[PDB]
Image (cartoon, rainbow over all chains, first blue to last red; front, top):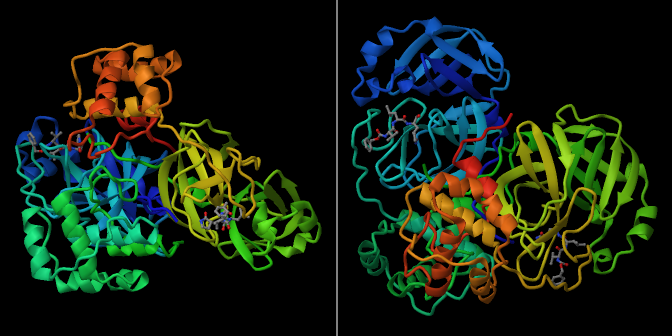
Length: 306
Length: 306
Ligand SMILES: *[C@H](O)[C@@H](C[C@@H]1CCNC1=O)NC(=O)[C@H](CC(C)C)NC(=O)[C@@H](NC(=O)OCc1ccccc1)C(C)C
Ligand SMILES: *[C@H](O)[C@@H](C[C@@H]1CCNC1=O)NC(=O)[C@H](CC(C)C)NC(=O)[C@@H](NC(=O)OCc1ccccc1)C(C)C
């Protein structure tokens, strides 16, 4: 038993990380087949970033201005183009470590693993959630741009996030691998509002089911509630409204534990109204919302990949 | 900025995981050079585990009774031996993915990454700490035995933990890679006491320094204290006594932030005496003790590996 915030094994993604240099700026790229993907602001000076005209800046660049370095293997750039907020550098060599992969645009509330990288070398791996306001709460320093977020289905890596920027909150924003930002953000050094965040209700419930599976059951109360009744408590505490789609998603956990979803909702409602009274659930004194129902099920059934 | 519980990239360790079968029992092994390492209780039936005579049980086994499977590559076993609580199976093939490695016995309070595995295939990676009572708080199901904990120094993997068992607490116990248990535990299905745990004071302070680096500074109070004065508050709250060795270890963080260690201790003392009053630090409502001073420094300086 036990329950931990667990990332996917990162080996398949490690083999794809490269270093991309244009001028003095160096960031990370993702090398898949014969294309390297990276944030387009690799082409900016520090001053350009205040208000860059990326088309005009890219026109001043040629293939040989982009230095792509894979460990010490170094790649010849034979084409470049800008797709939304990413650059695609065509190289003369296919990555021999390219895994089976897919580019996906994830939904708010979903989770993914991040492989944090600097100069094209991995530093660490951690799990998180795409917030409802399309930010993530990461750990990113200068030079981390181009680090990617991903999920694994057995042998297939689904890339879903590339890091671009940090917002005036210490939160982080980025794009999918077609270069479209999650949320309203633009890749410019100018003040930008994230907007109000909300707690991912279906993930909290999943985590309460995780708790029961692992023996933590003090919060299991006696009451029940209705969707409406719970959704009224939800808006007060800035939780996403629960839908029947969410109830259905929680079906397997409901069946494994014998606790109806609406009964679990009544427990959650009491936790929101009365707090935890200095107790903990799964080692936490806060209600956790960065485990999806799928995350809980894989961790309590032992799903593997390779 | 930002601060996350970050594991090491697991790729170098993924390449070493194999499946070991003896009879009906299947668990994970670690394949390094031409030796596979795994828990010796792979040789037990469910009934043997109540009180196994491992020498007598191993004598009934021959090389061909051990099935070692690496993905679908499958290895010929040409020798076996028992070292403390691990078996060493000699195979006829050196692992072509063997990283530069070392076997280390870590100290209580140190951290390491765990690659959780089933049937020799990785499922997830997460960070944790060797508790002062020589347990870990992991996420482990049936078949996870043989999963390993490790740290990376650039290109060198230091293996420090192999998983063996779960205790009547939901906590976990295991051995170093020479097969010596951390703590008083034995590999038998019989009730076993872990003993009182304590909080890793130097790690809490490191995490408070992390908080200040990332802007969370509300807890920075006005007072100071002495080691003695703080250590008296320490024993009351079941914290490890702080030593001058710990103060010295915290030197770099003290210099980076301009906060004397004893000033930070006075903040910690007030947090222990008065709680957090419903506030949070680095997104947590509890005092966190599973980041070492080194963990904080690598995460706020961007150290990489490969
Ligand atoms: C790539 O290096 C990446 C790393 C940053 C540095 C620290 N944490 C990170 O994630 N970020 C960048 O260099 C960005 C380049 C832009 C997208 C051209 N810039 C930023 O992330 C900057 N943030 C920003 O401009 O967002 C809006 C804003 C907020 C507050 C004040 C002014 C603007 C940050 C370095 C501040
Ligand atoms: C290897 O499969 C490993 C996985 C376990 C299963 C669930 N979580 C885990 O980490 N554990 C084992 O099968 C152990 C084999 C022994 C070491 C021969 N057994 C255990 O971990 C058992 N625990 C145990 O015997 O510890 C002492 C004890 C505690 C409470 C009651 C009785 C004894 C557990 C499966 C209970």
